[PDB]
Amino acid sequence: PVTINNFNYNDPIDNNNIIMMEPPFARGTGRYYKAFKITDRIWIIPERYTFGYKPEDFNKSSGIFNRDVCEYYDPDYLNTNDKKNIFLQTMIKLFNRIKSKPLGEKLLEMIINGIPYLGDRRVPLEEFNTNIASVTVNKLISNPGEVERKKGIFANLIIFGPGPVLNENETIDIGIQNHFASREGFGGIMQMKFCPEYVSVFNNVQENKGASIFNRRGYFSDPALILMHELIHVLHGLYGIKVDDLPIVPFMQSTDAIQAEELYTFGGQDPSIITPSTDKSIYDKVLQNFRGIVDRLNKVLVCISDPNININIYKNKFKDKYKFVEDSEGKYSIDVESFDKLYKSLMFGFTETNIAENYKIKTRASYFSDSLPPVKIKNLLDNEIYTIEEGFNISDKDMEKEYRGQNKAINKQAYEEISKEHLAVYKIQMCK
Ligand SMILES: [Zn+2]
């Protein structure tokens, strides 16, 4: 069972749930940020994602005429201790919403149990190595005003605040010399840029299909589903199955090329436009990568960075993670049936579509959908607007039927239009 911890931003450092941790991309460079353990292996650093970005990238465009309504900027987001607390409490509420039903509970469990392999492709077949950015992150164990002393701890996911564009949530993996452990069967510490308030809007759905122009319905997204979408990428990245650069050329609304990774993650009727050949090659690549992991497990003898780590305990943890089988002599191998079940679970089981169906959340029909302007949700921490159990679609307020709590024309008090330009663009899109 998954426990979702509680803390406030101003709560003191305890070297358990609240620490100073050095993120993966900042490894070796003694910069530590206040990190909060929301569940085992999952941390939240309520700061803006600045990796590979300059401070000027965070600024808004020079004026209204050159603004892009599809891309929202605000350099003042997360600038105070109180804004960093609002972020943490919103994340705890969203995580509590994810575990409120069986599907999301298992998603969090699969993420937690999906520990990165103790190594990558550079590591010898006979060794486990924890001294890399994709397996461990440094924790500051010394008090302020003392010479910095560290300890490497295991982690699976680190969620940060947004990068320059607030409404563009993204899950990132670690690359070493254009090779990602998260795409090679190993798995690796995943990172995310997340923003709960600025959500996506759509009008693609099963309705509107032939319906009158005035009777066209436009809805806003639930921040929990948006988070669950990104957590599926984390899952693929933790099990070493993230599909690398593979664009797919095409109900549906857009004909534009999209990544294979994004299609499987969205799910529903999306994996159907993928040629049976491409679909089979993605499956075969995962098998070949898992075959590499099993060969390593059969050859691993020592842990180079941690000669204390018990080889048998970790081999067993990896046997459970990848659902490998063992013979009478201890030798591991792949069982096609258990592999098929795990594969179908990671790629087709945990999708945005059936998470949306199970949670009564409204989402778009296809990923091949038009980008509508984002909207800002004023307060997610108010139960009169948003709940852990039901979302925006609250039963008492008659928002549970026809997903009316997500309908922009109906639940006008749950959100606010970012600008007059955003509304003007939305009105043209709703009535083409
Ligand atoms: Zn995505």
Image (tube, rainbow, N blue to C red):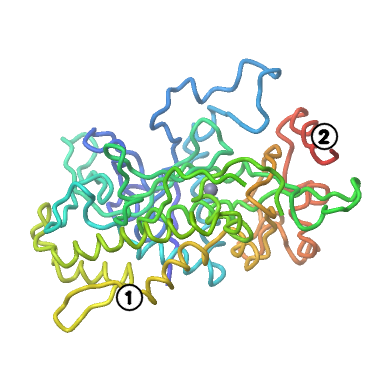
Decide: is 160 above or below 208.
above
Classify mark 1: helix, strand or loop.
loop
Image quadrant holding the N terminus, namely: bottom left
Left/right placement of residue 3 relative to residue 313 reads right
> Measuring 36% from the left and 74% from the top, which residue is drawn there?
336
Tell me if mark 2 has few (under 14), some (14-19) or many (20+) residues whose alpha carbon lies within 10 angstroms of its own. Answer: few
The numbered disc on residue 326 is none
Q: Quadrant of residue 67?
A: top right
Q: Nearer the viewer, residue 244 or 232?
A: 244
Compared across the picture, whether 27 is left or right of 248 comes to left
Give residue 111's quadrant in the image. Answer: bottom left
Nearer-N-terminus badge (2/1): 1
Which one is in front, 78 or 222? Answer: 222
Q: Is residue 315 left or right of residue 228?
A: left
- Where is the C terminus found, in terms of image quarters? top right
Q: Residue at x 38, y 49 (%)?
A: 190
Q: Secondary structure at mark 2?
A: helix
- Which residue sits at x=74%, y=53%? 406
Would you say the beta carbon of the disc 2 residue lies within 8 angstroms of ligand 1? no
Q: Position of residue 94 (x, y in %)?
A: 55, 56
Q: Is residue 429 left or right of residue 361?
A: right
Find disc 2 in the rendering and name its residue: 428
Measuring from the top left, give residue 180's x and y in whole percent: 32, 45
Q: Which mark is residue 335?
A: 1
| 231, above or below 322, in the image | above
